[PDB]
Image: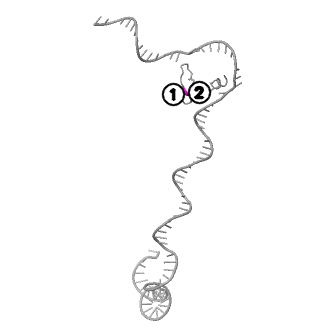
Amino acid sequence: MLQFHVATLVDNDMPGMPRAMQKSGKPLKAIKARLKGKEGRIRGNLMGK
DNA sequence: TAACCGCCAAGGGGATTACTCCCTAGTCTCCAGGCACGTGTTTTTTTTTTTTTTTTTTTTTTTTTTTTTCCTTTTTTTTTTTTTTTT
């Protein structure tokens, strides 16, 4: 479970790995979700601020 | 009905004796295939690296702008206070 919490802190988009459960019925938004994506920290905040 | 026996007749060829002769038994002497020893080159086995297709993983999906709506927990177990009954 410690490895599960560490992995979901790092990457919650890993297939074959149980998704982290948030309080509002959503998956947890990890740091990879903050960076990778069109609306991410790179494309939506550094590329397109 | 001709096997078998008795009787008679005839002849054919194996046994016997002698002479010969010739092929093998025996004995040297030279030499060469038959055999004991060593080994091989194909045959099978095992690795080794690649090949080729299948399967899985992962990442991706034009940009900008303006309005609402709903939600931003919830049941389920444990605890703690309160109230009632009894001696």
Say whether residue A18 is visible: no
The disc placed on residue A4 is 1
| Tag in front: 2 or 1 | 2
Helix, strand or loop for disc 2? helix
Name the residue at 51% across, 28% down: A4
The disc placed on residue A13 is none
Closer to the camera in the image, A20 or B85: A20
Tell me how far mark 2 sits from mark 1, CA to CA. 16 Å
Helix, strand or loop for disc 1? helix
Vertical placement of residue B44 versus B85, above or below: below
Find residue B14 and report its horizontal and vertical position in percent.
Answer: 45, 85
Name the residue at 54% across, 26% down: A9
Q: Mark 1 lies on which chain?
A: A
Find residue A48 and report its horizontal and vertical position in percent.
Answer: 67, 23
A18 in magenta: no
Are callouts 2 and 1 both on one chain? yes
Closer to the camera in the image, A36 or B36: A36
Closer to the camera in the image, B32 or B15: B32
Answer few, some or many: residues within 10 Å of disc 1's Cα (few below 14, many 20 plus, some between 14 and 19): some
Q: Which chain carries label 2?
A: A
Judged left or right of residue B87, residue A30 is right
Amino acid type, residue under disc 2 in the picture: Lys
Q: Which of marks 2 and 1 is nearer the N terminus?
A: 1
Find residue A1 and report its horizontal and vertical position in percent.
Answer: 48, 27
Name the residue at 59% across, 25% down: A33
Find residue A23 and report its horizontal and vertical position in percent.
Answer: 53, 19
Mark 2 touches mark 1? (CB < 8 Å): no
Residue identified by numbered label 2: A32
Quadrant of the drawing holding the C terminus of chain A: top right
Answer few, some or many: residues within 10 Å of disc 2's Cα (few below 14, many 20 plus, some between 14 and 19): some
Q: Give the range drawn in magenta.
A: A1-10
Amino acid type, residue under disc 1 in the picture: Phe
